Amino acid sequence: KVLKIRYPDDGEWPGAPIDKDGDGNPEFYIEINLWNILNATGFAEMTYNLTSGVLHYVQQLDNIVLRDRSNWVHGYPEIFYGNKPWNANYATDGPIPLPSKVSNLTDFYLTISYKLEPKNGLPINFAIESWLTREAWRTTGINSDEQEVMIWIYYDGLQPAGSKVKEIVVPIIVNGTPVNATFEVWKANIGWEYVAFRIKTPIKEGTVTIPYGAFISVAANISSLPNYTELYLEDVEIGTAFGTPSTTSAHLEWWITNITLTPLDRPLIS
Ligand SMILES: [Ca+2]
Ligand SMILES: [Ca+2]
């Protein structure tokens, strides 16, 4: 009834599928994903109670030494749907058929209920991201002619890579109320094209619904990549990037109670 993964007990890359009906196709996949930590004292643990659906992350890391300080953040503990293109983990038991070409995929709402508790000023975000690849089912990383799209609905003390492009309005729902929100749009080239949408009014807890195609449409429109609509939207990842090169301790707790993807009768890109 409770799935648990733990760093460092389960190795340096703990992860596991959430497969509540035991059918061999996960509905989501969880990873502690301390991808830029070389060594730390303490632990990080992610539990997932299969009756309530609560995902709970608890992290107490100290003495942190990074694998590469130029990558800035320490890690991105996360839950995702679809095929994460960096590894062989996937989750496809859901209503949206990911991966799919962006030219074929319906728009969808993403609704997340959550609560974040970073300790002592730790720089963090709460970031949803997707990877857009030239092949349907990538598992070996990302190339220069592909894209990372990130949507930050909370942040403290972190700025997206690259430089600010513009601000956009996106109609979202916060705590049951439809609201026009503003997102800054940032663009970088970091080995691949990077586009991040950073909310101007961070939301540290509650229930948030966003229309995914509002973001992908802007990412398409500002992209320098050729044949953008032939890319596959591989996945939707939800997690908290944290840390900076001068952070040596990182204590953080958070909870996610619901993730829902809701299809809409319309194209993703408009
Ligand atoms: Ca399943
Ligand atoms: Ca994968």
Image (cartoon, helix red, strand yellow):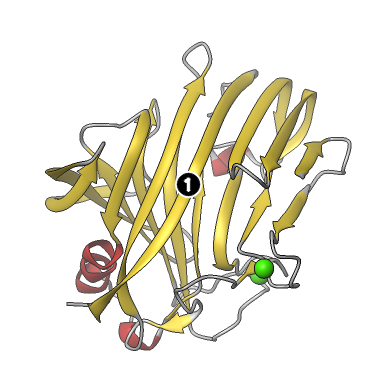
Q: Name the residue nearer the viewer: 131 or 9.
A: 9
The reply, left or right, for residue 243 in relation to residue 265 is right
**Residue 133 seen from this side:** yes
Question: Where the C terminus falls, by quadrant?
Answer: bottom left
Q: Where is residue 211, by image quadrant?
A: bottom left
70 relative position to 225: left or right: right
Frontmost residue, 163 versus 116 = 116
Question: Which residue occupies 45% across, 83% down?
Answer: 100
Helix, strand or loop for disc 1 = strand
Is residue 242 visible in this depiction of the protein? Answer: no
Which of the 4 image quadrants contains residue 114?
A: top left
Quarter of the rendering occupied by the N terminus: top right
Q: Residue furthest top?
A: 120
The residue shown at (22%, 32%) is: 201
Left or right placement of residue 95 versus residue 83 in this view? left
Determine the residue positioned at 59% across, 45% down: 53
Residue at image coords 31%, 43%: 208
Image position, residue 61 (x, y; %):
71, 22
The image shows residue 160 at horizontal and vertical percentages of: 36, 43
Q: Is the residue 94 above or below the residue 244 in the image?
A: below
Q: Is residue 139 above or below residue 171?
A: below
Q: Quadrant location of residue 49?
A: top right
Ligand 1: does it lie within 8 Å of the C-beta at label 1?
A: no
Within-10-Å neighbours for mark 1: few <14, some 14–19, many 20+? some
Question: Would you name the residue on which mark 1 appears?
Answer: 258
Residue lying furthest front in this view? 51
Amino acid carrying mark 1 in the image: Asn
Q: Is residue 195 left or right of residue 190?
A: left
Q: Quadrant of ligand 2?
A: bottom right
Coordinates of residue 92 in the picture (x, y in percent): 59, 73
User: Can you say whether 240 is above or below 102 in the image?
Assistant: above
